[PDB]
Amino acid sequence: SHSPAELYRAWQDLRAERPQLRARDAAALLQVSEGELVASRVGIDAVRLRPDWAALLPALGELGPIMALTRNEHCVHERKGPYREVTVSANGQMGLVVSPDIDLRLFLGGWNAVFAIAEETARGTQRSIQVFDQQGVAVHKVFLAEASDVRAWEPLVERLRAAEQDAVLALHEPRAPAAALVDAQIDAAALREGWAALKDTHHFHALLKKHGAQRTQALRLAGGEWAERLDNGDLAKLFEAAAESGLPIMVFVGNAHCIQIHTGPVCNLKWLDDWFNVLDPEFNLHLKTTGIAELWRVRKPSTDGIVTSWEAFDPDGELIVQLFGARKPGEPERDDWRELAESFKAL
């Protein structure tokens, strides 16, 4: 099949031929995961680190301001700031990074392997920490930038360096995807009853599971007072409306293992072909809009009152991006967000 040497050389040949090709896409062309592709760099310009998240994550704090990158297939979220304040749960399975800038929810159980990369650029070095999941798909990346404290880099790598620089990566076949039930098999009245009774928006996943519903399926069955379809193009328009007023918003972008959040206004917006982009000094968002299959306005009750969000999904029903109004927990959402989010007409 492939040795890692062969894979690295195949990869570099592709890059010579097509430098627009990002690692994620190169891996797919080479019939491997991005994680395997990165593992082929070990001994060249990468070092394998121990998957010791409770040691690694707080240590990223020593690097000073960084850029954190979390993405899914259709949307990329890049946020600048220091990697703090980190907390990791007692059982090691949940991590949080809480601050005005870097704002993360980390689901550590699926985090498999991590590499420190120090890549040579034309008279330069780009340093990053890159995490991959049990299928080798990227989870989360942290890039050093101009303001980073490079002095902390070598000691961090030394501290966390794995004993076995293999390099080959160990992966697992995904868990059974439960067959989805058809809408008619869901108890719509009970789901609607529980939806109306929601007390905490964090309790929403449990509600879906209680009734065996997929997320878009629940939205279809919830009724218009709770959830309505929107024209897919309205998402970009809401961003444009939000930039005009300077309204603070929250932008959530995640995958199965990591969710990254921006809180604040958005300012500089740009279309380039089907890419819709936020291009602000501390936050970049890159959204491949043709990847949006469905867009929903969603209303959920809670102890703090109704919370209104917009939720965009791909055609596999997975979330691309979610928008909320800025609010501190315990607060109601702001009227200006609620108006904006309601201002677009349902399908």
Image: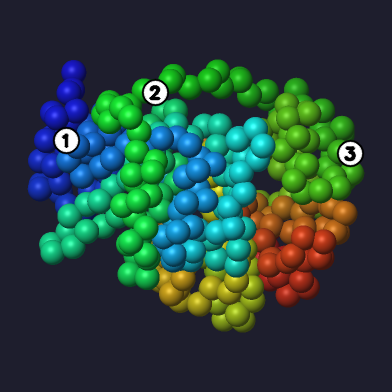
* Residue 8's disc number: 1
Q: Answer left or right for 346 relative to 303.
A: left
Q: Is mark 3 on a helix, strand or loop?
A: helix
Q: What residue type is labelled 2?
A: Leu
* Residue 256's disc number: none
- The residue pinned by badge 2 equals 171
Query: Can residue 76 be seen?
Result: no
Instruction: Judge depth for marks 3 and 1 and give the one in front.
Output: 1
Q: What residue type is labelled 1?
A: Tyr
Label 2 and label 3: CA atoms lie apart by 41 Å
**Residue 170 versus residue 309: which sits nearer the camera?**
170
Which quarter of the figure is the N terminus placed in? top left
Q: Is residue 241 above or below residue 346?
A: below
Point out residue 224 in the picture as x, y percentages from the top left corner: 78, 50
**Residue 209 versus residue 117: which sits nearer the camera?**
117
Toward which corner of the image does residue 161 lie, by quadrant? top left
Q: Which residue is drawn at 13% across and 64% down?
A: 123
Q: Which residue is drawn at 81% across and 65% down?
A: 331
Label 2 and label 1: CA atoms lie apart by 19 Å
Q: What element carries label 2?
A: loop
Q: Which residue lies furthest to the bottom in this view?
A: 245
Toward which corner of the image does residue 36 lie, by quadrant? top left
* Residue 193's disc number: 3
Query: Can residue 225 be seen?
Result: yes
Instruction: Judge depth for marks 2 and 3 and give the one in front.
Output: 2
